[PDB]
């Protein structure tokens, strides 16, 4: 089997991407944030505290003839941005782009933190990291990809995120028309539950490539590119007037600037992030200070190849017995 679904930016900055997902019988379509940095499929629901719902579409398990309470199961998750959610668990039929999994754990939110309530465009998350990170207790549950894997034509999914435009998540096949050149594959460590890999270095603009190992994660659920402070300083030093602002929470730059590109290494190959992808717009409405798309990871504990980096590439998440990642230009 295969599946193919379009993923669409939630706003003009590409802050996140939503993909329609069918849950239950008859289908209830929710727009979920596909997140290769976590491993829970959770949704706003008829059980979510009413004051914490503000415009999201909800899953109502009582209206699904295939929903079953997973008795005794609870979940609770906290994300790197400080947000969180928790609740109980149903199993139900879940389909993405024509690919159907029966018996998928659908985690129903009883509580969500304010940033989820405040974002009316995201109805939940669909985790695509390794199932060892799934938070369901006392019986850990499998991701949608883990459940689908054996049925797929090939045990892979791909992320093709757009810049200010829709893109595609495919399951079970590699669309050879969706990228240019060849796909370069690189080793993955699953020891932390992430799609963790080592970039071979970087360049700023037209500058020379610096060969240096940068361990980090491919995370579609994180907006920006988080890298070591040395690398980030070298980037922003090429932008007149750019500075790190403690009050804003990162590097800012004059909105009048033209930003240089940023290149990262994948083995001997190179992925170029155009400068425009690094512009996240005014820090507040009407400001001439703009927020940067490359930020320091120093306070995180891990480097994160988020959407800023991934949307410059066609990315293969290879879930073979020994997983690997592939990157191609596009």
Image (cartoon, helix red, strand yellow):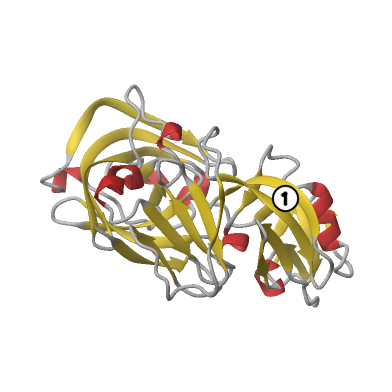
53 vs 7, nearest the viewer:
7
State the SS at label 1: strand
Q: Residue at x 52, y 57 (%)?
A: 326
Residue of label 1: 227
- Residues 38 and 205: in front is 205
Vertically, is 41 above or below 86? Answer: below
139 left or right of 64 in image: right
Residue 19 sits in quarter? bottom left
Between residue 137 and residue 211, name the one nearer to us.
Answer: 211
> Across the whole image, how many numbered discs are drawn on residues?
1
For residue 98, which quarter of the picture? Answer: bottom left
Q: Is residue 261 above or below residue 211?
A: below
Residue at image location 81% in from the left, 73% down from the top = 206
Q: Position of residue 15 (x, y in %)?
A: 56, 61
- Please provide percent x and percent y for residue 64: 15, 47
Residue 236: percent from the left, percent from the top? 83, 62
Q: Nearer the viewer, residue 76 or 199?
A: 199
Q: Is residue 268 above or below residue 47?
A: below
Residue shown at 65% from the left, 70% from the top:
277
Q: Position of residue 80 (x, y in %)?
A: 59, 41
The answer to whether residue 280 of the structure is visible from this angle is: no
Question: Taking the image as drawn, is residue 321 in sight?
Answer: yes
Q: Is residue 227 left or right of residue 117?
A: right
Residue at x 45%, y 50% (from the top left corner): 117
Q: Quadrant of the N terminus?
A: bottom left
């Amino acid at each position: 089997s295969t599946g193919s679904a379009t993923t669409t930016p939630i706003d003009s900055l590409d802050d996140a991407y939503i993909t329609p997902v069918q849950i239950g019988t008859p289908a209830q379509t929710l727009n979920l944030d596909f997140d290769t940095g976590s491993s829970d499929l959770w949704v706003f629901s008829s059980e979510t505290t009413a004051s914490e719902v503000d415009g999201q579409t909800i899953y109502t398990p009582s209206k699904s003839t295939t929903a079953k309470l997973l008795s005794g199961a609870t979940w609770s998750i906290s994300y790197g941005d400080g947000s969180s959610s928790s609740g109980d668990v149903y199993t139900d039929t879940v389909s993405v782009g024509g690919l159907t999994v029966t018996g998928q754990a659908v985690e129903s939110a009883k509580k969500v933190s304010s940033s989820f309530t405040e974002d009316s465009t995201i109805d939940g998350l669909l985790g695509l990291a390794f199932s060892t990170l799934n938070t369901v207790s006392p019986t850990q549950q499998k991701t949608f990809f883990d459940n689908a894997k054996a049925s797929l034509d090939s045990p892979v999914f791909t992320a093709d995120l757009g810049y200010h435009a829709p893109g595609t998540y495919n399951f079970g096949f590699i669309d050879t028309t969706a990228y240019t050149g060849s796909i370069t594959y690189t080793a993955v460590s699953t020891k932390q539950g992430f799609w963790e890999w080592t970039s071979t270095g970087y360049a700023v603009g037209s500058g020379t490539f610096k060969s240096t190992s940068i361990d980090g994660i491919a995370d579609t659920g994180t907006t920006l590119l988080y890298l070591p402070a040395t690398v980030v300083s070298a980037y922003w030093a090429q932008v007149s007037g750019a500075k790190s602002s403690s009050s804003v929470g990162g590097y800012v730059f004059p909105c009048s600037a033209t930003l240089p590109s940023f290149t990262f290494g994948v083995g001997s190959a190179r992925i170029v992030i155009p400068g425009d992808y690094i512009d996240f717009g005014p820090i507040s409405t009407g400001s001439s200070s703009c927020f940067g798309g490359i930020q320091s990871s120093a306070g995180i504990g891990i480097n994160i190849f988020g959407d800023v980096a991934l949307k410059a590439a066609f990315v293969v998440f290879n879930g073979a017995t020994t997983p690997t990642l592939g990157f191609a230009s596009k």
